[PDB]
Amino acid sequence: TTPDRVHEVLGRSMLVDGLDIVLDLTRSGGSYLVDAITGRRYLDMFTFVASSALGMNPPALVDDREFHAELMQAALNKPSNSDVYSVAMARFVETFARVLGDPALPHLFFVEGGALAVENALKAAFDWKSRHNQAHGIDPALGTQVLHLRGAFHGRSGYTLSLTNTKPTITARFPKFDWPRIDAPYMRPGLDEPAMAALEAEALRQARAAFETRPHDIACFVAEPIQGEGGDRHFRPEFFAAMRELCDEFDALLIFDEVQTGCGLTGTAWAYQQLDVAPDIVAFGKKTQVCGVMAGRRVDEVADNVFAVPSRLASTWGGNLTDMVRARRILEVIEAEGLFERAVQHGKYLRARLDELAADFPAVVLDPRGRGLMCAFSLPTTADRDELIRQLWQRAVIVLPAGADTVRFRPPLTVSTAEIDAAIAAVRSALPVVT
Amino acid sequence: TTPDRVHEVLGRSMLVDGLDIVLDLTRSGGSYLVDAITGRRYLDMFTFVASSALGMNPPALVDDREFHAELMQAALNKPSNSDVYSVAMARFVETFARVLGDPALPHLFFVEGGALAVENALKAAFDWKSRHNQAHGIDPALGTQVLHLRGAFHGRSGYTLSLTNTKPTITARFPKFDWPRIDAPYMRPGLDEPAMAALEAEALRQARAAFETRPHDIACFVAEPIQGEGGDRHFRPEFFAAMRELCDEFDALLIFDEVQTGCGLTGTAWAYQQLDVAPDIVAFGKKTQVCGVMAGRRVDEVADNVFAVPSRLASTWGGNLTDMVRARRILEVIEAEGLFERAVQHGKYLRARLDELAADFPAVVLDPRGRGLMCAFSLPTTADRDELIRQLWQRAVIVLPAGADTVRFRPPLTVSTAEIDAAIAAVRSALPVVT
């Protein structure tokens, strides 16, 4: 089967609604994807839906003969890491703890898939609340609900379908729990400190009302620190700081879903580190390759929590060993080359360019925003946004939509300023055409 | 970090309740695992919880230089296969369809994880029932419940926690849907045709009552063709044939969870092929490396089902590309070496040996049973069963428990008769010690 027959072969078995290209696995590199059909190079601001930290075929992985041997050893088989331990696994775990670890969150758990990472954070909270209730004379049947935000995306699995609320297509006709959902007080243009404070106060009021009308039954609050799929919606640290206090007042855990924000994209290991709010549990995935949770803080106050008791959380494989070996090497590169700091600096650059675009096209380029390399802007209508994406595709630049009117940038951590300039140049070319 | 420090390193971050050994990834091969600490070889009747079809480091994969290059190309990166197609992916899909495909079930969907494979089968059914209801004048809010069996294991995710019912430890304190659950009329010793028929009739009665008291609200019936974790419980074809008719009468889909039974273990591609019952959806995982569903039959009667409409089912990665490349090669070996037939023949051999054990130890070795290489026997008590497993471990044979009193055999498809003899010899040595 040849590159030009790929879409035909897949089309016999599946819906083929992806990109028009066929990925050349060998010739792609860094910030560029190569179409195996034409040999055309595409500038990658999409990074497999923000799951690639270093881009395709990074030199530090490709040129490392010792790593090749390690990777090959892992890739030939697929052990059940939950039952059977290896040096390859232990090396990954120790470097994860070193590079991304938080001393307050020592409990680590790994699984395949971002939705399942979030689910296991939820399971930890449900167990914790039930047991905490029981220890304080409250019915252990209580503690089954999840406070969450409007516009949230946490995945497409059994529990996360009850949380995710972006496009109706994702959740329609699937059974859901009736869990309390509150307004998301995200930052928007033309709102000053007092205006933002009032918006936050209303979400806080709704949150308080949920806790008070469902006594002892809310196990946790879950949020993305920055809402990705919902449209790159940013929140003030003040909002999460207030939620942290409110969670503590009602003995509920605070969970950050860092599946999209995590592993350096915002300029720190985790976005929460810049918001100065301490979570009890963090769910991670995408860039980490293997998914999972880190837990601690109040979790430890219940001695028989799911991290202390065998067989409460599990899967067959306990994450993919190949992903663990790849991730170990990726984390070593991040640490050695100071890629978090590079993300801060290049992120400031990208943001500055988007500000310039907003000045040049004031009625078209709206609400330029970002933290680190996680940047976005919006257009007046969905039609304008969709057209800009088509125009960029024609110019060999890959970006992703979000929400009704957002264009998202998700470059690799290794993106150069010249590559950012190229992306911006394409947007500038395309804009007069869309207007 | 050295083999002797693996448990210490992992123990800082996780609960370390797995096997005492450290897996040597290089020296393990075929039906043998190697402990990196001692160099002791362990006879493997466990195969990473039945997820290894060919055992460790199969020669056809290890000696194939062309495959090495293909695997390395896949392993270096992790593309989002849902968005971005490759030759490596298309080759996997076409060989999957060739080797394991069913002409009645042309729709394929891939995902990481067995629980998520089952969840996507459920999502397909929920959507189908709602839309089928709508097309026939019935409220589209109806069609949200899942008929399932006692003793079932379908995973540990949001929807599957409402189905799984083996050990309380798996499901306690996690929120569940109230879905209808019926008795499992599995075969047991000392029950003749009429006795089995009466047991089945009672389960059928319970099933009928569920359909009639929850009108238009049961979307599907889900079952394992042979219950694995619940204790290798086998069902007569007559039971599933009756359930098939009953599902059709009430316009509900029939889903087989073949995550444990699938990919040749029972002697055919799928266990359902030997039961002569046609499912609408099959969920697969474990041995297939990449997980997912095959769908067809009645699914196609709803033209806007989830396999026809974009973005109803999805994940970031669409399965792991490394797993796809490995699985392609594994399937080619199965096809080329006639491993399904080998499983039939060696399975008959293993079963014969267990019958002999039952004759020699009539009060201790109970209910010897199996289909293909999926074989088991039971002991009088849980204490006897647990002790036998410890005694086998001491003799370097790895087997898995199931239920309260079952010992399961899960050899690779490539197991030899001498290796089966070795396993049986160890059981014979251990039994006088446990009695």
Image (cartoon, coloured by chain):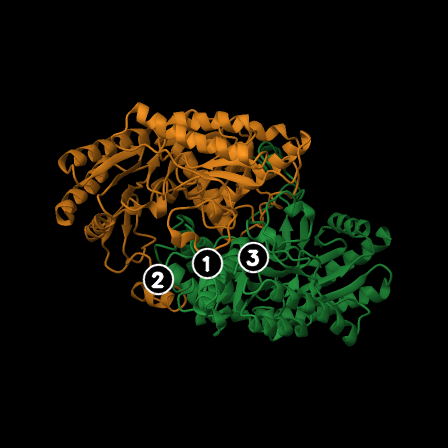
Chain colours: A orange, B green
Tell whether A338 sits left or right of A364.
right
Q: Amino acid at mark 3?
A: Lys
Name the residue beneath numbered marker 2: A16
Residue B391, x across and y down, in percent: 78, 49
Q: Is residue B63 visible?
A: no
| Residue depicted at x 45% and y 25% | A242
- Quarter-wise, where is residue B276 in the image? bottom right
Q: Report helix, strand or loop for mark 3.
A: helix
Question: What is the distance, in whole Å, between disc 3 and disc 2 at their CAs?
Answer: 25 Å
**Mark 3 highlights which residue?**
B286
- Disc 1 marks a residue whose amino acid type is Phe
Which subunit holds the residue at mark 1?
Answer: B
Q: Give the chain of mark 3.
A: B
**Numbered badge on residue B110:** 1
Label 1 crowd bin: few (<14), some (14–19), many (20+), radius 10 Å: many
Disc 3 packing (10 Å; few <14; some 14–19; many ≥20) = many
In the rendered image, residue A306, in percent from the top left (x then y), is placed at 62, 38
Chain that bears disc 2: A
Say which of A293 and A320 sits in front: A293
- What residue sits 82% from the left and 69% below the top? B190
Q: Residues within 10 Å of mark 2 (few under 14, many from 20)?
A: some
